[PDB]
Amino acid sequence: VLSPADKTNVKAAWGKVGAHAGEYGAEALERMFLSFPTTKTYFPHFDLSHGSAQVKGHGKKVADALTNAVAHVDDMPNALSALSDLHAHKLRVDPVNFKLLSHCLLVTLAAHLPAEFTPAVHASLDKFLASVSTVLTSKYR
Amino acid sequence: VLSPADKTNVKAAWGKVGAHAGEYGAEALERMFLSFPTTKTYFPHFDLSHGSAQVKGHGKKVADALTNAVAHVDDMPNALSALSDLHAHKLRVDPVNFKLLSHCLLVTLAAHLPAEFTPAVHASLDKFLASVSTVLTSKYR
Amino acid sequence: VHLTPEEKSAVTALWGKVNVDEVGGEALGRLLVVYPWTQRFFESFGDLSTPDAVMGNPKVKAHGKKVLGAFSDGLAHLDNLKGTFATLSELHCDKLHVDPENFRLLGNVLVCVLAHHFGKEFTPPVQAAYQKVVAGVANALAHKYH
Amino acid sequence: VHLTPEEKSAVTALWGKVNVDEVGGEALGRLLVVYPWTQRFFESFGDLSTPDAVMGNPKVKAHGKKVLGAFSDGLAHLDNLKGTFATLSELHCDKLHVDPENFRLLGNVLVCVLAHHFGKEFTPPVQAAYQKVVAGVANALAHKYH
Ligand code: HEM
Ligand code: HEM
Ligand code: HNI
Ligand code: HNI
């Protein structure tokens, strides 16, 4: 469960991300495809190389979903309901992959947020992304 | 999310286990220590010799906790509260290991329930053990 | 990765008693029932709507036999699983787009199926040897991914 | 664990700019903050009760120096990580009783610390090379467990 301090940290960190959320979403995806090639099995229809137009667009979608989760941080199971259904039933992405994108999102945040990515904030963001991942895999079976 | 149908399957299967629970708990631990030797890093203080009474005693405790969880399957976060506290705050077992014990519990059940371990029941028991594991790791951070 | 002579003998002894058809069909069928997201690769197999439908599906049975047949062949190459599965690894990566986590899931389902079939004969040491094998086979099938 | 020549050069170039003592202390501290169950091995280290207590803990910092110093030495032996880390693997198993999952967690924390320190210089291709390294080191440290 996210603590009061976790929620303050997540809101502050994502607040600082600000207008860059879409850029950072695309960067995290790029980092994932390069670092964890098995995740590419889910995107055979995508151009997955650097500067991909599909990846830039998709990163905006991912970022928007995260922004919404931050806005509804006390009701993520419901705020992410449709997206959980999509990943569980249409896409059927193996749950193991959510930790890979989560890690790539943390790395991206670290690379852009020198003052804000303190150990406490890192810890809170990891918990937050774990919680998003848990919600997104809650309807698989 | 354990469905009412899962709960039906779990209750029926564990009912059949009956007084063999303690024995199967010990067997599951033995299987885990042999099959997944990294789990032994949590038990360096134990006697792990063949037929260890310490292991057998511990299997009985694991089994009793599961029997309680089955009996309170609608209310597992409450039933397991003290055990969740213990694993989170004292034992501090990495969450990855819960899947290893759960698998060994399934294998043990399979080995002893020729008639009852249907595909549907296998699926329900896997979900149940994953739910137990979720409750036991819920307070870790 | 590296099996001891005692582990190898335990693997080979059990396998000589395995009905690859029943075990293969049972393992693939249970993979699809227990982890239903794995059905994503098999929509062409037809009706996968209930457990009974999955298990009795002729295409699931045929594919399970084929998969476990290749697994069985792999047991003759316990010291070079990576070499032997190299071709199949590339195929599953590039042509079939199968996440290698699926091999790990199948391996654990296979262990459950062996336990279900053999009962007390599937002892904890026999299981432990099989866990090494299935981990090795999954790793070998994952090894050429890119 | 197969790095390209370009990846090997990028690993070496970045590492030449790393203060190993500092980065080691930071990575071990972040491990104990982010995944607080990992504090279970460090009862003797004193106060670990808050993020600041952990990060500034002199015993944590001293230990991080040792750990990353061994890691750094391993980067000279990328083609033989298993041999390089064999005695440390045996030690962490037989004497220290450290679950090898901890090595995987530390690897990913280290990648975060490198990103944090280097900013834009820690590019997606540089990260990808470090992911290969950190997976290889964790696998090597787990290899002699039994
Ligand atoms: C933090 C975790 C994740 C979030 C917030 C997220 C969010 C999203 C969103 C917002 C969409 C678009 C939904 C729509 O079009 O209606 C999407 C689609 C998709 N996601 Fe995720 N996702 C996550 C994790 C993953 C992972 C780990 C994978 C696989 C490695 C994955 C694979 C896909 C695929 C294949 C699509 C469909 C792409 C297409 O349009 O063809 N997602 N995701
Ligand atoms: C299904 C999941 C699990 C259940 C139901 C369970 C149950 C229990 C119970 C009932 C106890 C005794 C508590 C007491 O004395 O008050 C216990 C203790 C313990 N458990 Fe678990 N446990 C589970 C998972 C794990 C896992 C995965 C590990 C590590 C591989 C583990 C390691 C331990 C250890 C080291 C102790 C303390 C033993 C001692 O020194 O007395 N547990 N567990
Ligand atoms: C859940 C996915 C999945 C898993 C777990 C799996 C596990 C394995 C394992 C593991 C022990 C082995 C040895 C193996 C072997 C094979 N697979 Ni896999 N395969 C999987 C998805 C497939 C798919 C999909 C095909 C194509 C079938 C078709 O319809 O053509 C396939 C085809 C094959 C073929 C046939 C290739 C050819 O045409 O030459 C073999 C042999 N395999 N697969
Ligand atoms: C969270 C657990 C944990 C992790 C992730 C970890 C990860 C690593 C990694 C990974 C890159 C390396 C190369 C490494 C190297 C070392 N560790 Ni690890 N160690 C860990 C827990 C320890 C413990 C515990 C000790 C003994 C500490 C003490 O109290 O003296 C230790 C001791 C060492 C020593 C000193 C050996 C001795 O005392 O003879 C070295 C060198 N290591 N450790």
Image (cartoon, coloured by chain):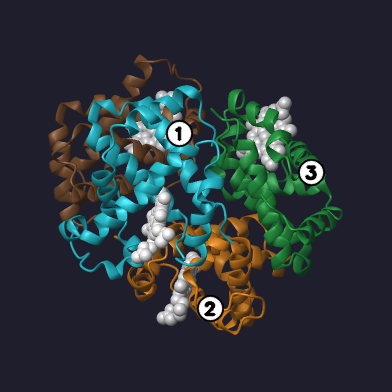
Chain colours: A orange, B brown, C cyan, D green
Q: Three-letter amino acid code at disc 2?
A: Phe
Q: Nearer the viewer, residue B118 or C18?
A: C18
Chain bearing tag 2 is A
User: Which residue is depicted at the point 47% across and 47% down?
Assistant: C138
Q: Position of residue A85 (x, y in %)?
A: 33, 71
Q: Nearer the viewer, residue A108 or D145?
A: D145
Give how far apart the Cα atoms at labels 1 and 3 are: 29 Å
Q: Nearer the viewer, residue A93 or B102?
A: A93
Q: Nearer the viewer, mark 2 or mark 1?
A: 2
Element assignment for label 1: loop
Q: Three-letter amino acid code at disc 1?
A: Phe
- How crowded pointer 3 is (Cα within 10 Å; few <14, some 14-19, many 20+) is rated as some
Q: Check whether the beta carbons of the residues at disc 2 and disc 1 lie within 8 A of each other.
A: no
Q: Can residue B86 be seen here? A: no
Establish if A133 lies above or below C127.
Answer: below
Establish if D71 lies above or below B54.
Answer: below
Give how far apart the Cα atoms at labels 2 and 1 are: 38 Å
Kindly identify which residue carries mark 1.
B36
Chain bearing tag 1 is B
Kindly identify which residue carries mark 2.
A46
Mark 2 CB lies closer than 8 A to ligand 1: yes
Give how far apart the Cα atoms at labels 2 and 3 are: 37 Å
Mark 3 CB lies closer than 8 A to ligand 4: no
Q: Would you say B109 lies left or right of C131 here?
A: left
Instruction: Report which quarter residue D140 is drawn in.
Output: top right
